[PDB]
């Protein structure tokens, strides 16, 4: 049988009963542990994940965790994982620093269980908001509108795997949409959409590429299995950056790759409130189209709306492997700065 090349993510329609289970489990964990960063909760995370998640989610995520086959896209859309009460959530804060984690506590529990069922362990990075906790609120900040960050809006966020500049980048990501009233499409790009290993892709296994953090060590864009590889890629940071410092050969290879890759980008899915996108950060890159925060256009008219709000959680399947880059007193806190180099604070 000829290979069925994946061009889009797996879509799971979460049922009302599953949504009810998740809500009650979220509430129980809040009462039992206070918050999702409780060391007793984190230490018994996988036990809580397999015992408390709706069983179909547990089966999906378990299958996904160990699936690096030719058929695997590397992303799952869980449609309507949660019901967001928009009025209780109230207005979106001016930036991520104004997020009410007391209100997002239950969501943090739900997201950590999803990672826990992979199985994978939520982690935080000093490279991202000086850690900023296991759960990040991704909000369009008017001051950062034209930036190539999660606090951006007016500009296209070109496809990238999270933290391509780190040797210990996240294994898994979850993006929980609380609101997307601007109807911003989610953009995904899978290395598996290319199909069979070709000459353009083979050049990416060479450890000759700059992975700029946002004289420098170089890394491979493709790694892992030679036939069915893993990817570390950031189009904006490695290609569309004058200060990337790529060699003539490396830039050519990346340009050739980008030409082939850009035709495979999937921007079909527009997330709704309560959808969660779950990603294997070694298989699938993500991005977001340009938008004006707090508005959408319908019939050539501007409809004012509440500003985009999404929750991001990152995880690693092994605490052992990352142990030389984590805090002595916190094996879930990654202190890596750039491709092996650790942040030198004092
Ligand atoms: Fe990202």
Image (cartoon, rainbow, N blue to C red):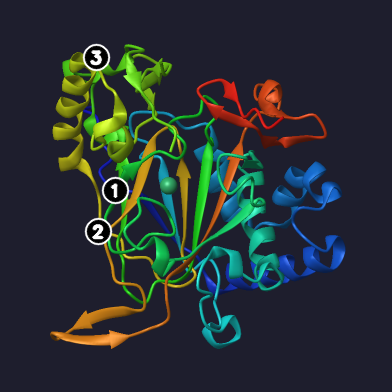
Above or below residue 34? Residue 319 is above
Closer to the camera in the image, 204 or 74: 204
Q: Label 2, secondary structure: give it.
A: loop
Closer to the camera in the image, 145 or 22: 145
Q: Of the numbered discs in the image, which one, if any, rests on residue 268? A: 2
Question: Dot 2 surroundings within 10 Å: few (below 14), some, or many (20 or more)?
Answer: few
Q: Label 1, secondary structure: give it.
A: loop
Q: Residue at x 42, y 71 (%)?
A: 308
Q: What x and y, as percent, mark residue 100? A: 65, 71
Question: Dot 1 surroundings within 10 Å: few (below 14), some, or many (20 or more)?
Answer: many
Please give left or right for residue 230 compared with residue 247 in the image: right
Q: Residue at x 34, y 34 (%)?
A: 71
Q: Label 3, secondary structure: give it.
A: helix
Q: Of the numbered discs in the image, which one, if any, rests on residue 321? A: none
Above or below residue 76? Residue 262 is above
Closer to the camera in the image, 180 or 65: 180
Q: Is residue 71 visible?
A: yes
Quarter of the image where the C terminus is located = top right
Please give left or right for residue 290 compared with residue 69 in the image: left
Which is closer to the viewer, label 1 or label 2?
A: 2
- The residue that label 1 is drawn on is 8
Above or below residue 35? Residue 261 is above
Which is closer to the viewer, label 2 or label 3?
A: 3
Alpha-carbon span between mark 1 and mark 2 = 9 Å
Q: Of the numbered discs in the image, which one, if any, rests on residue 203? A: 3
């Amino acid at each position: 049988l000829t290979l069925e090349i994946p061009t889009s993510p797996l879509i799971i329609k979460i049922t009302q009963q599953e949504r009810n289970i998740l809500s009650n489990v979220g509430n129980l964990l809040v009462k039992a542990f206070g918050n999702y960063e409780n060391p007793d909760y984190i230490a018994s995370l996988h036990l809580h994940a397999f015992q408390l998640l709706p069983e179909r989610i547990t089966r999906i995520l378990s299958q996904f965790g160990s699936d690096f086959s030719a058929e695997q896209y590397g992303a799952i859309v869980f449609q309507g994982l949660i019901e967001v009460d928009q009025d209780d959530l109230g207005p979106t804060p001016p930036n991520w620093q104004g997020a009410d984690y007391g209100k997002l506590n239950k969501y943090g529990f739900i997201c950590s269980l999803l990672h826990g069922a992979v199985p994978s362990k939520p982690v935080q990075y000093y490279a991202q908001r000086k850690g900023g906790g296991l759960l990040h609120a991704v909000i369009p900040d008017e001051k950062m509108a034209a930036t190539q960050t999660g606090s951006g809006s007016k500009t296209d966020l070109f496809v990238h795997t999270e933290d391509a500049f780190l040797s210990n980048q996240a294994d898994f990501l979850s993006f929980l949409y609380l609101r997307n009233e601007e109807r911003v499409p989610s953009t995904l790009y899978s290395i598996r959409s290319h199909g069979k290993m070709n000459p353009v892709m083979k050049k990416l296994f060479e450890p000759i590429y700059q992975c700029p953090k946002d004289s420098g060590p170089t890394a491979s864009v493709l790694y892992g299995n030679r036939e069915l590889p893993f990817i570390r890629f950031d189009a904006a940071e490695q290609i569309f950056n004058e200060n990337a410092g790529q060699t003539s050969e490396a830039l050519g290879n990346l340009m050739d790759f980008w030409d082939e890759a850009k035709t495979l980008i999937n921007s079909d899915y527009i997330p709704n409130s309560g959808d969660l996108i779950f990603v294997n950060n070694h298989l699938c890159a993500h991005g977001r189209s340009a938008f004006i925060a707090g508005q959408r256009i319908e019939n050539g008219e501007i409809i004012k709306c509440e500003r985009r709000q999404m929750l991001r959680m990152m995880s690693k399947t092994s605490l052992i492997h990352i142990r030389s880059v984590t805090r002595t007193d916190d094996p879930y806190f990654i202190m890596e700065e750039h491709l092996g180099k650790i942040f030198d604070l004092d």
